[PDB]
Amino acid sequence: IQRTPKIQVYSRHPAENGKSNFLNCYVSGFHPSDIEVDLLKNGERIEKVEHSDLSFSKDWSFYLLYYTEFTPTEKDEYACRVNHVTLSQPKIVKWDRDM
Amino acid sequence: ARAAAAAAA
Amino acid sequence: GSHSMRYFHTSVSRPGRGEPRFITVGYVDDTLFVRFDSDAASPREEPRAPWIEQEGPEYWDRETQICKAKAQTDREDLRTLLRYYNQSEAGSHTLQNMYGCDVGPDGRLLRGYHQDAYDGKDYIALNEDLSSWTAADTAAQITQRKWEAARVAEQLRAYLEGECVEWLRRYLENGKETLQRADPPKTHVTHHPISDHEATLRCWALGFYPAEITLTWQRDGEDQTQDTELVETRPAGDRTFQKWAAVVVPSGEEQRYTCHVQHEGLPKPLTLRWEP
Image (cartoon, rainbow over all chains, first blue to last red; front, side, top):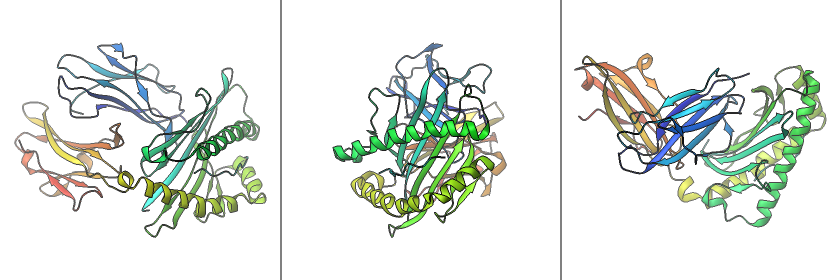
């Protein structure tokens, strides 16, 4: 079976401009496990990004946390970009500090 | 601690 | 039940690219404590929680041997299943296995698990009796007969009743100060105007452990079931979790709405309101 990833983009702590924090991209519910995830700053791929090791839920679909350290500002635009066999093109979900 | 049993399908 | 231990395993064939990739992680409750990735330089099982690092060199060696042995058995099992389902060697395939135990406050087994899936669908599972099998199709029925004849359920049962429970209680005691403490959610409500006439009220539950939590919205004490947007509980990345629930309300009606939070870290379920 194949399943498309749910995606949530959010920070570790309540965003405070000027304050260091962590940008998280959580992908879940997908199948197969092969997936490509990037965290984007102003459209550009942030290079040093970490991820957990592949694990899965009771229904066998996969989940992965990807993250990086960041310092939000008013200006900088952050997003998560996901590529998976179920997606005809990569899904870009923008970081909203309210979500 | 993991199970050591090695079973095959 | 009261506590649990689980091991997760995934092998993925990579035709034309390499040996199958194998990844396995273990959890006690919602805490990751070990990982093994066959694609790591000189693969070894590695600690991922503070309280497991005290185990000695024989622990890390035996766990690594088990992992490389499972990585090999899965490779063979990937070959077997291509024969059982008459598939080509050119396609990629996934084998997943999860087994583990739940114990009650008595510290005795409440429930054991051992189940497998092929390409994301159920293949064969050990029943709650830790004695019989549920096979999901006729290929898995081949496995079932072989596993009945080879008295495999009996070996898993001895493990789940014994070693599983015994080392879980070991992990629980050594990691007591983090694993036996529930971290209650930090909650609050935010307000997000949609237009001049409506706004979203979002009820946040942050920094909590374990993952299980209930968040609900009520208008004048009635449940806003088909009207709440409830995201999936998500890792903050520091071993605790986050969750929020939202509802869109008419401007001026905000103070009729209540967020209600249940979590075992709370003495009683919370009620919160937007405090403007």
